[PDB]
Length: 7
Length: 8
Length: 246
Ligand SMILES: [Cl-]
Image 1 (cartoon, each protein chain N blue to C red):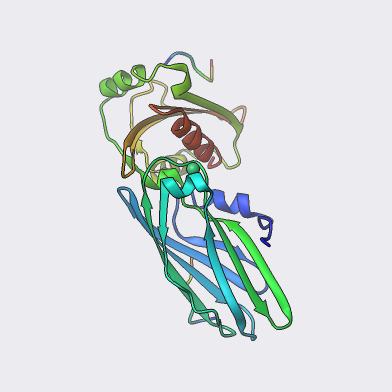
Image 2: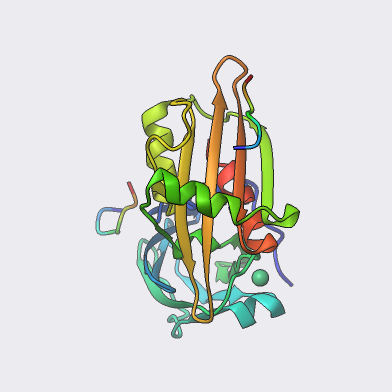
């Protein structure tokens, strides 16, 4: 995925 | 009422 | 005239998105219950009306009301219901449902009747929603990521970030995603806290492949949901429906 909700 | 279709 | 949507209509509507059976409306006079089933682009919904009183309802008139666009996308067929409902009696109708194309609006069920010297008028949103035609698609991780990447146009993705209404209970979440109509794909997102889903919306005229990712933050009590589908309106509709379930 491009980015994550939780770092 | 008893007699009715229920939705539980 | 038509009653405005009953208090709790929207909250209750949301409880019929991932399940088919329940009480849609109840006050001191009347209980409205639903049981439905769906297959491919079709459905069958039983609507039950229970008179909780010792007095007859006369001119008992349930009407399914659909906006113009909705009618082109969704065919509802049902028969006359007898206008007299005896005290303590429960009566019913069958609604045969055919999804023609993807749709965003919901029908309104309006019920009017005489009760003694009074006139009653109740309006509730009827939970016939696009995901009722959503059926699961099992697939391997490799295929999921291929398909995800094929849905890279900005308008194909819709996201929401929302506060959890319910405990972030892993097993219940899995069950709700399945009940929504999605497959639950394990070991796709390498973070095991996240949930990944896939399915196909079945309509008479077209089918739409849909992918989803649900990311919980248990510390923060919030979720991010991402939908990707080939149709912006479908991504929006499924995202907004599914967002209200957790
Ligand atoms: Cl619509």
